[PDB]
Image: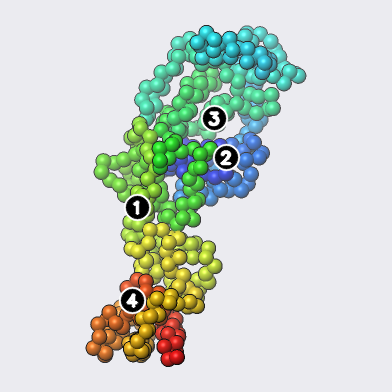
């Protein structure tokens, strides 16, 4: 079948470019009814703390990228790395060497001076049955002496690299742990990986890994190497530079799919199409078709597509995510409007769900403060009269609703031979305390029957004083 993986080197969280890598590995698998696995490099026993790897698991969780297998931990496979090196040894396809760090520097110094790229000359390739003390003990892989290794990278095409300028790499360390390159091969092979989608730093490594597959007698995966993402200014985006954490987009209150749409479009396209559903991406995405030049961030673009989905999605889909942003502010939700009803009111006025909750709190708690400017729209007494009328009729039929309040409010503005301009203006100050809110029916409605009536009286008893 198709087997992809996402194997991140645990930092504090899931970096946005990791998210994209994971997205593509996830689509490639799902698309063909394949399996998508997740590995975790927890060999440091620091860095990878449970909070650090939960920040990854929860990041993937929120985005919707689920894995058929794992998370499968590098610590669980220490002795598996150990045994495959020993197998490689017994088969004469890897050797030990014992050069000191001082000795190795001498070779980097002797190599760079000739204008040749530093290698480890095969000084121990045919000999010692070493072992023991000498903490410089390293197991090195016998990389083929001559020729080339070549692979059809699905993105970058034919890459051919010569076996000269690929040295006999260390594959197993003195601390009982594999070198990076060996492990990814041991991992990919043991996990049946068929398509290895990764950033283009590792393109130089691929040939080494290929030669290790070959010695192992293992199927070589297809490789897909992509230009990693650029900073909004232009710098390359990375963990050392102050990178965008994906979870900061949950808290900023962008919709999850809005982001995977946003991500997908960095470095991939389908002619003129900018908005894909979860299906449109399964059906149309190909990892072949990712653009050979690096895509750049555009938080402006993100803002738009987030609004499109705010506007266009089912408000019930958005309801629980608003309840995330609302709950953050200390709100007792059970005593307020439905989140979905708020969505409908605010979705065309706000760019993020955090903007929305900030603007919706007025509905969800009492009306403690009034903007002084806006109360000088009670100024007249003749504010008492429209509010009193609003109040009378806002005792509307047991169907309390946007529509139900509109008619009531339409019927109050007439009883006074006034524009709805005049009934609504102070009524906005009564239930909001400010001159700004959605259309009055929406806002009168979001307070609830009880809440409006309380709020109106509260304004009325203030005006009578």
Q: Is residue 11 above or below residue 167?
A: below
* Spot occupied by residue 269 in the image (x, y as percentages of width and height): 31, 40
User: Does 385 sit left or right of 130 as displayed?
Assistant: left
Numbered circle sitting on residue 305: 1
Q: Nearer the viewer, residue 71 or 8?
A: 8
Numbered circle sitting on residue 393: none
From the image, tell me which residue sits under label 3.
184
Q: Quadrant of the C terminus?
A: bottom left
> Which element carries disc 3, helix, strand or loop?
helix
Marks 3/1: CA–CA distance: 37 Å
> Which element carries disc 4, helix, strand or loop?
helix
Q: At 49% from the left edge and 62% from the top edge, which residue is drawn? A: 324
Of the residues under marks 4 and 3, which one precedes in the sequence? Answer: 3
Marks 2/1: CA–CA distance: 30 Å
Marks 2/4: CA–CA distance: 50 Å
Marks 2/3: CA–CA distance: 15 Å
């Amino acid at each position: 079948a198709c087997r992809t993986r996402f194997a991140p080197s645990p930092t504090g969280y899931l970096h946005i470019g990791g998210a994209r890598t994971a997205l593509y590995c996830w689509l490639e698998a799902r698309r063909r009814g394949g399996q998508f696995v997740l590995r975790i490099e927890d060999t440091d026993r620091q860095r990878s703390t449970q909070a650090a790897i939960d920040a990854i698991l929860e990041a993937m969780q929120w985005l919707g990228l689920g894995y058929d297998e794992g998370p499968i931990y590098q610590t669980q496979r220490v002795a598996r790395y150990q045994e495959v090196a020993e197998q490689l040894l017994a088969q004469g396809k890897a050797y030990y060497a014992y050069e000191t760090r001082e000795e190795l520097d001498a070779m980097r110094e002797a190599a760079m001076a000739k204008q040749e790229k530093p290698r480890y000359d095969g000084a121990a390739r045919e000999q010692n049955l070493p072992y023991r003390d000498d903490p410089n003990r390293v197991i090195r892989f016998k990389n083929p002496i001559g020729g080339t290794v070549v692979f059809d990278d699905l993105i970058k095409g034919r890459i051919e690299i010569a076996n000269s300028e690929l040295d006999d790499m260390v594959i197993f360390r003195p601390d009982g742990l594999p070198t990076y390159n060996f492990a990814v091969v041991v991992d990919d092979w043991d996990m049946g990986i068929t398509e290895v989608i990764r950033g283009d730093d590792h393109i130089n490594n691929t040939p080494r890994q290929i030669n290790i597959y070959a010695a192992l007698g293992a199927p070589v995966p297809k490789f897909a190497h992509m230009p990693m993402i650029l900073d909004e200014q232009g710098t390359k985006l990375s963990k050392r530079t102050g990178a965008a954490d994906v979870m900061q987009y949950k808290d900023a209150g962008y919709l999850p799919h809005a982001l995977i749409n946003y991500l997908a479009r960095l470095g991939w396209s389908h002619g003129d199409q900018e908005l894909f559903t979860p299906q449109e991406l399964l059906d149309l995405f190909d990892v072949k078709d990712v653009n050979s030049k690096a895509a750049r961030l555009d938080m402006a673009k993100l803002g738009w597509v987030n609004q499109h989905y705010l506007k266009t999605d089912d408000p019930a889909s958005i309801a629980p995510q608003l309840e995330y942003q609302l709950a953050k502010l200390g709100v007792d939700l059970a005593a307020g409007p439905a989140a979905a009803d708020v969505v409908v009111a605010l979705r065309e006025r706000v760019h993020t769900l955090k903007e929305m909750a900030e603007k919706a709190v007025v509905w969800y708690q009492p009306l403690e403060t009034y903007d002084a400017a806006a109360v000088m729209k009670h100024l007249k007494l003749g504010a008492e009269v429209p509010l009193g009328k609003a109040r009378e009729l806002l005792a509307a039929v047991d169907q309390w609703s946007v529509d139900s309040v509109s008619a009531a409010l339409h019927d109050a503005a007439a009883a006074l031979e006034l524009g709805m301009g005049k009934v609504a203006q102070p009524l906005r100050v009564a239930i909001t305390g400010t001159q700004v809110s959605p259309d009055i029916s929406q806002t009168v409605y979001l307070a609830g029957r009880e809440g409006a009536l309380k709020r109106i009286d509260a304004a009325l008893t203030k005006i009578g004083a």
